[PDB]
Amino acid sequence: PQITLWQRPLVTIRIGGQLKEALLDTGADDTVLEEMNLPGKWKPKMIGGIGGFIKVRQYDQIPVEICGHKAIGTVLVGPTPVNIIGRNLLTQIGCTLNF
Amino acid sequence: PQITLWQRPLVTIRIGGQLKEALLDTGADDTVLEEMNLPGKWKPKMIGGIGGFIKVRQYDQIPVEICGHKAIGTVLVGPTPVNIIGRNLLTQIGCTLNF
Ligand SMILES: OC1(c2ccc(Cl)cc2)CCN(CCCC2(c3ccc(F)cc3)SCCS2)CC1
Ligand SMILES: [Cl-]
Image (cartoon, rainbow over all chains, first blue to last red; front, side, top):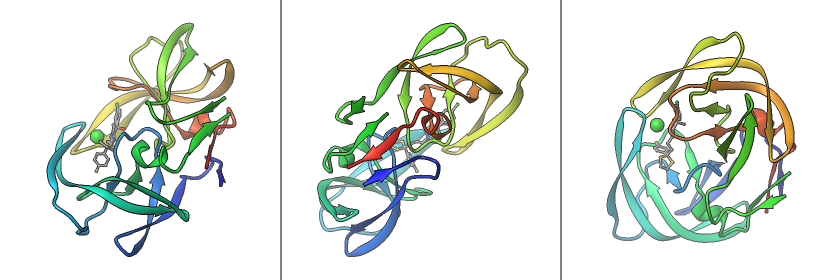
């Protein structure tokens, strides 16, 4: 679909049998989702920001359905203040920026 | 242009006479650029991140060329690691998300 950017680009994602709201973010390398447990083993990952680090868990071949489009990739789960779809899942649904 | 997201969407912008490389970021509401000496009156601003805040200089009707498209808007200037051009200027150049 065409998403203009006057409002935050929030969409629905179905992941782990849950329907959640997430931000399509071209400035994120990785996808970061609010806490939940998924199927599989997880690798600890410590992600950074401005005055520190946050520990998150990395799950690896998770099916996600972003606005009906199925995509498979790595998801990081942890205490994020908003669900963020990073470029790793945006490339999978063939999303481009256009102007 | 139609830009794909396999690599970081970095573009050449022109602001305050100097050329810069910046990240097209749909997740960020604002445009935050590195220290440059912009001519103009400014206000201090705080932008929060992981466990803290950083102070920047808010400038308000700045002309910014982004891949030849001129846009006018607010730019926050300060110790950013990464030059962010967010939604406030992406709407101005007619940038969309499409899939
Ligand atoms: O924009 C920032 C900023 C930039 C400049 C200035 Cl001056 C101030 C603030 C402040 C916000 N962070 C967000 C980190 C993005 C990632 C992440 C998402 C959620 C989460 F809980 C943890 C990490 S997304 C994947 C890895 S980090 C970047 C720099
Ligand atoms: Cl941060």
